[PDB]
Length: 331
Ligand SMILES: O=C(O)CNC(=O)C(=O)O
Ligand SMILES: [Mg+2]
Ligand code: NI
Ligand SMILES: [Zn+2]
Image (cartoon, rainbow, N blue to C red; front, side):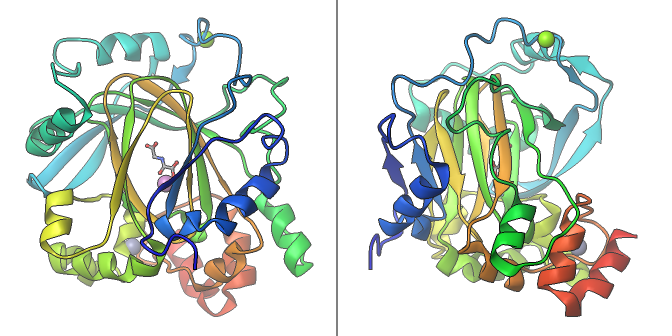
């Protein structure tokens, strides 16, 4: 069995290997990359996502989210308070202000220590989940707006044609902006490209150990657990590496820098934080190996998780028994 310790693998495809996205994902899996839940892909030196980032300031962040924490430094939840719209140029200035800017630090490890010590005492503002793309239309390789769609994958594998679309999302971050512990909708893959700016630190639990994280989360968030049998779908809970180590939960960590891709694999729980002003682009995708994970994915039916239009068909076809209850949660 390849990668039996479930380490995060880093790949350096050549320009030739970067042509066929599906084939390269299947290659990485042949080497055991999925066992970590997360992989890093450094693009060939010849590749670029677009020519420059000099003209992005007028993108609108219609609903910036202030991430307010409750709890203790290593075990907290966050809620998202909606703020007034602002442009990317306005948000970048805000991120660089004395109130929000990255503190002085020695290295990524020192910054990670400072994040876990101090995150809860501040409320950073995240421009998340903005439909759109920063890939140039002429970029033909690993262009996250030109991937094969999940609807077409389900149709190719299972023969059933379904409604829905699959488009990318932009994330504008600042110091301390935080992504809570989650797997993807329907335990899909994700791919994330850091277009510009400061790094993003990731934590990940191997898919084969995901239920260990869930059991810890039910212990640490006991009211939330009673409310919903899949409350991590709410994407609000944080647990620090120190707490994970104290409770014997297997995980790994890695820092993504600008110009790098990360792939999350089906049922790979992940969480993380931004080091400073940055912009990422991410999208869900599927492969044949996902189908079995989609069929088994947990679902939130309490009403909190509220998701895209396109998840309807995935539940309806892959999880017909759960469909009625889940749809009640959506309505
Ligand atoms: O970058 C972020 O805030 C969160 N991204 C992801 O969870 C991802 O790409 O799956
Ligand atoms: Mg612009
Ligand atoms: Ni994710
Ligand atoms: Zn729920």
